[PDB]
Image (cartoon, rainbow, N blue to C red):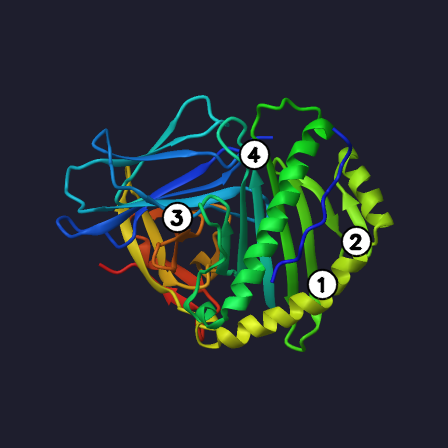
């Protein structure tokens, strides 16, 4: 259960480039149906246009994940489409974003314990196009379990995991109505931040909050979060002592001084130590079965033939959960950290993740290299070698 937010009240009335990977859900064999993904990350502002192209031409039925953002405030989203890969068909993903002069097209190539309850809030103004879009997204240990999105005709808190369905009607009504009250607080703050940052009234702007608690096995609060960003930059944050605020710039000093006078750190302390902890506990009971599951990586090495007497070994980790993983190549028992290539961990789209690490080795020397896979679901690290 998210807190009811206090208005920022900063006083009476910057862009990040997307990163793109394009890859299939399952290893591509020609003729068999599959899923092509276009994973876009690290971008701000959140408005973005993503097209998937087949042989130069737009692909019509392209589904898209709901948009999320990460602890560094940048947004991310998964686009995907069904496709049956063939030998000569070319696929690609094209991204239009205000941080880029021109749309970026990225082609697909067929080779190359403690617990937390956190809420991720977004409010984006859209002058001329509608009311600000407001979202609340709840995560129990990085698993999304509830969501409120204002862009519906009758906005409602929705379960996002089957184990939330057992909460009664009284719960969803209370959350829904708290969300609509929260929505109005951010609408007012979006108006007000314009003056505070001396901005024009026709531009789109963004408020983001991360709010919640991390709780140890003993049931005691390990860390509390209440941090705000305006246009993708720190604005204000409760300190680890849960008594004082860190204001990232001058406009936030007005909010801080105000929240000091109002005792807002103390209201947060109480929510964080009590209410947040107690609800986390409740969501853990409901989700007991599913939330604790891990899936360990199945790994394998692939071989790719380069110019001259160099070859590339690629080490793959597929179908693992959670996303945290380490891949390393070794030669003679030393790690080749400084000369190997790797991709950012990426969702398969069925709820699990993929990663690979590659190294360039001499032709005929493939059996001198060993790949290591470290994942928390493994009883023991995996060790693998290329094999024909």
Question: Would you call the spot at circle 4 few (<14 residues within 10 Å), some (14-19), or many (20 or more)?
Answer: many
Residue 232 is left or right of residue 385, and the answer is right
Give the image location of residue 266, x and y in percent: 81, 59
Residue 264 in picture, x, y percent from top left: 79, 53
- Marks 3 and 2, Cα distance to the nearest angstrom? 35 Å
Secondary structure of the residue carrying numbered label 1: helix
Instruction: For mark 2, give the secondary structure.
Output: helix
Q: Quick check: marks 4 and 2 in contact, CB under 8 Å?
A: no
Q: Mark 1 = which residue?
A: 271
Residue 111 relative to residue 44: left or right: left
Closer to the chain start, of discs 4 and 3, is 3
How far apart are labels 4 and 2 at the CA level?
A: 26 Å
Q: Which residue is mark 3?
A: 65
Counting residues from the N terminus, which is met first, the one under dot 1 or under dot 2?
2
Residue 138 sits in which quadrant?
A: bottom right
Secondary element at tag 4: loop
- Residue that numbered label 2 is attached to: 264
């Amino acid at each position: 259960s998210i807190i009811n937010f206090e208005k920022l009240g900063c006083g009476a009335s910057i862009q990040k480039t997307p990163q793109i990977q394009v890859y299939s859900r399952h290893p591509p064999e020609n003729g068999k149906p599959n899923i092509l993904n276009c994973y876009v990350t690290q971008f701000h502002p959140p408005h973005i246009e993503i097209q998937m192209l087949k042989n130069g031409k737009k692909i019509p039925k392209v589904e898209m994940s709901d948009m999320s953002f990460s602890k560094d405030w940048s947004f991310y989203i998964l686009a995907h489409t069904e496709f049956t890969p063939t030998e000569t068909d070319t696929y690609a993903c094209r991204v239009k974003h205000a941080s880029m002069a021109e749309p970026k097209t990225v082609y697909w190539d067929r080779d190359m314990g403690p617990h937390s309850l956190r809420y991720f809030v977004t409010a984006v103004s859209r002058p001329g196009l509608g009311e600000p879009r407001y979202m609340e997204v709840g995560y129990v240990d990085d698993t999304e379990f509830v969501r409120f999105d204002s862009d519906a005709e009758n906005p409602r808190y929705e379960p996002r995991a089957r184990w939330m369905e057992q909460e009664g009607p009284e719960y969803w009504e209370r959350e829904t109505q708290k969300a609509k009250g929260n929505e109005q607080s951010f609408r007012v703050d979006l108006r007000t931040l314009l003056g505070c940052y001396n901005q024009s009234k026709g531009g789109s702007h963004t408020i983001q909050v991360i709010s919640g608690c991390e709780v140890g096995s003993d049931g005691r609060l390990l860390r509390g979060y209440q941090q705000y960003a305006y246009d993708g930059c720190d604005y204000i944050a409760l300190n680890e002592d849960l008594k004082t605020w860190t204001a990232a710039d001058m406009a936030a000093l007005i909010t801080k001084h105000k929240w000091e006078q109002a005792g807002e750190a103390e209201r947060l302390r109480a929510y964080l130590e009590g209410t947040c902890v107690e609800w986390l506990r409740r969501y853990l009971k409901n989700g007991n079965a599913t939330l604790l599951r891990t899936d360990s990586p199945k790994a394998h090495v692939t071989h790719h033939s380069r110019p001259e007497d160099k070859v590339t070994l690629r080490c793959w980790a597929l179908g693992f959960y959670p996303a945290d993983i380490t891949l390393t190549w070794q030669l003679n028992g030393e790690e080749l950290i400084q000369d190997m290539e790797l991709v950012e961990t990426r969702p398969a789209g069925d709820g699990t993740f993929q990663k690979w690490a590659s190294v360039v080795v001499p032709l005929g020397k493939e059996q001198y290299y060993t790949c290591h896979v470290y994942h928390q679901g493994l009883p023991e690290p995996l060790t693998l070698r290329w094999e024909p």
